Amino acid sequence: IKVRENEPFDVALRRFKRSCEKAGVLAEVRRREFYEKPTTERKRAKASAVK
Amino acid sequence: ADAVKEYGIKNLEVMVKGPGPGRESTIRALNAAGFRITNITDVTPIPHNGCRPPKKRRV
Amino acid sequence: RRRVIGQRKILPDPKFGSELLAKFVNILMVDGKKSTAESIVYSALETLAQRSGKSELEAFEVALENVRPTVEVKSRRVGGSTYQVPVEVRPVRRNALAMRWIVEAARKRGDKSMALRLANELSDAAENKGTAVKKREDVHRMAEANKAFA
RNA sequence: ACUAUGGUUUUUAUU
RNA sequence: ACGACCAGGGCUACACACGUGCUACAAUGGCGCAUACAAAGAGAAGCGACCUCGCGAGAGCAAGCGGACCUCAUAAAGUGCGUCGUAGUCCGGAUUGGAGUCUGCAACUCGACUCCAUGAAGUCGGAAUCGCUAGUAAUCGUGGAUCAGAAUGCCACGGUG
RNA sequence: CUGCAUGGCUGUCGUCAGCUCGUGUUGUGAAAUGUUGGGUUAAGUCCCGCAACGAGCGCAACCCUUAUCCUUUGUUGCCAG
RNA sequence: AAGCUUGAGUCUCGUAGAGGGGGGUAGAAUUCCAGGUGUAGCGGUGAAAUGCGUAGAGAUCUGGAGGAAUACCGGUGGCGAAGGCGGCCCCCUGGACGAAGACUGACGCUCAGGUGCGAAAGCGUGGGGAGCAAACAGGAUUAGAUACCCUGGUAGUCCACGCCGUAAACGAUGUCGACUUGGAGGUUGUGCCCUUGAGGCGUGGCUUCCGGAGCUAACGCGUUAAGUCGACCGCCUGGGGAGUACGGCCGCAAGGUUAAAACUCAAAUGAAUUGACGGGGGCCCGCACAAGCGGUGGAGCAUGUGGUUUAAUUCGAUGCAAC
């Protein structure tokens, strides 16, 4: 995955590297992550869908 | 493009459909006819209609 | 694979001041007998300076930017099919290959001496209408000179 | 987007 | 006697083709002269120098050292000169033949060597197909064990590269 | 006579990176795991994950040897003076 | 023999949706019709040919005809006892569900025989016939080719009244009721709020995967159970044959129904572990290739296994690992 200027390097987290396919980001799978953080994010996106 | 010289075409818009190998040299051979080809659109599917089409079988 | 190395250390000739002419004694040469090819260095070239540059020290080196390749085509295989892929010549090999086949047909004929068969090869070096042209025209022979395979 | 054709092989101790 | 001494057969017999190697079909060739340089092995019925004679092999006379010293032993290719201008050829060698030279219990049979006489096929090869790394490949030289004698097999050492 | 009894040799994968085992761990169990994933290498080579951490054979260490420097012997080998 | 509301059933205003018909509403190109535009090949294959072509095959415009079929949206989303159901609107209609009140009053469950249902195929009669397509006839390729591949083509594919009830009819789980633990992601009502959130918090109806316990040989099943238990029905008792055989039934019929045995094996069956391997799914090296360059077998020599053979042509070795 890559978005915007990144390129020129570096802007941390580096998720265009070690790709290849399958089973990436597995240290953010099962428990601990998410909770309400994707709720507040997607509510602001829907508050930005108007007109 | 040699069969149309009596029509006096100047500005020309191009449409490209389908994945086949002849899809690029056909644009240079058309430039080599003396027409302004500043409009080129690709309209390849994204499939629609075809009745359904029927498919079945495997893979 | 795992080898690849590469390249060989070469110098200009001690007697002629040329980094090209030291390669010419390895051409039209057999069984390590460079001495038989030294007998036709500059001596046979008085016939060739009549149509190329001035003096024996440039009568081949003027043609250096023509007798070397810069682009080729390469044959590769996939499943049941064969494909002809255009390629660019790499810097160390682009600097080379000037004399590798430029006198290929002087080897065996039965007509005239080596010093004459050398001049009867170098006369076609910048013209390509004589003998063995398939050895030097090949680099465009799957490109511009024949488009039917594409 | 892509190569189309390989049948047959007649047996024995795990000291 | 399935034990093995003597005397002959053989294993080099050919009613089938073939595999690996060699050498040709040659002109950076072949033949004949000139010119320039080695490494490693071998030497007590030894290595055999030098010299003479015999188309020659070799025989006769006979030195020096049992070998870092004396000997096997003009390294060859490379360079130069002479030559054919591509002819079954100055190419090519199998066969049909002669006369000598050596060893050995003995060589007709089933050996080597020399100098000469005849000189075919072969014009780069079915269906196709082998191999490769840097003092190496290529190519041209040298030595040695098996021997009384006797390999294109076997094992090794230089040049040029 | 025959390795279809054996002392003892010897063929080939291959001189491949592979094969086992202590004390654990997995499964109902014979057994499997350790040695399969990740970055890497001539390689089970070196490291990280990870139910393993380690050990022996192969590999490697170790040892010889070549390209440099240093030193002992000199005719019959060598020969700058 | 009287009650109860707690299983079963009913009414208001409302709700999602490929449930089942019939009538409406539309287009595409292969096709067909006419008049134009307009041409040397068209089709297919590794490579071709049968076939179709200058008499226009091939390609295509314009207005008309016709048969199969419905992309998008459509989501690990719905409907239902299965089999089935996905252009769109309407009329008629089956099934299911919500808010708050009002009712019947055990009206419930299972089932021999009955009774009622079929995806696709086969069939009676009348329509249908673009594109494909069993059968059948040719072109390939094969010592076959009768097949895969290519060109044609009848039944079939569709419609309608019917005939025959088949299945991997599949989650291989007979039917019903109840108790037993959590998570993530979909999906549709409704109370209070003009949602003024692009909805929040209570709370009914549905719902795909994960998986604490329990079952199991292992796969699998999992509160949606193959778990823990009752109510009613039918099902096996060793393979090999075989729902085959004998008989009636019902169908025009292939079938469907209940359902063996002489003989034969004294045995078979289920799950996945380690080898062995692939004409697999992936990764890594080697003159295995690429690229360059020099050879081999035909002639004539040197020489030996196997074959021929005198009088013996000694034994042993015949895959990579003999000659």
Image (cartoon, coloured by chain):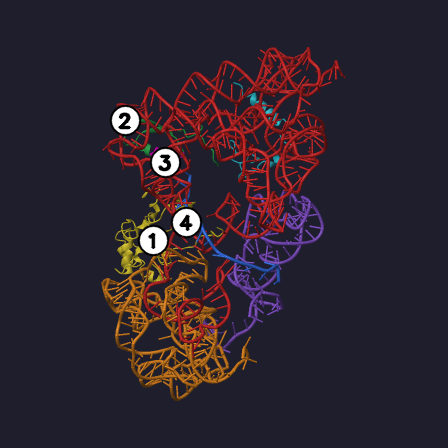
Chain colours: A cyan, B green, C yellow, D blue, E orange, F purple, G red
Quarter of the image for residue A47 reads top right
Quick check: marks 1 and 3 in contact, CB under 8 Å?
A: no
Report the Cα–Cα distance between label 2 and label 3. 26 Å
Q: Is residue B22 located in the magenta-colored stretch of the structure?
A: yes
Residue at disc 1, secondary structure: loop
Q: Position of residue C50 (x, y in %)?
A: 25, 53
The amino acid pointed to by label 4 is Val
Element type where label 3 sits in the image:
helix
Give the prevailing secondary structure in the magenta stretch.
Answer: helix
Of the numbered discs in the image, which one, if any, rests on residue C44? Answer: none
**In this rendering, which labeled residue sits more in front, label 1 or label 2?**
2
| Residue at which label 1 appears | C101
Circle 3: residue type: Gly
Q: Which region shows up in magenta? A: B19-28
Side of C30 where G236 appears, left or right: right
Which chain letter matches label 1? C
- Can you tell which quarter of the image residue G149 is in? top left
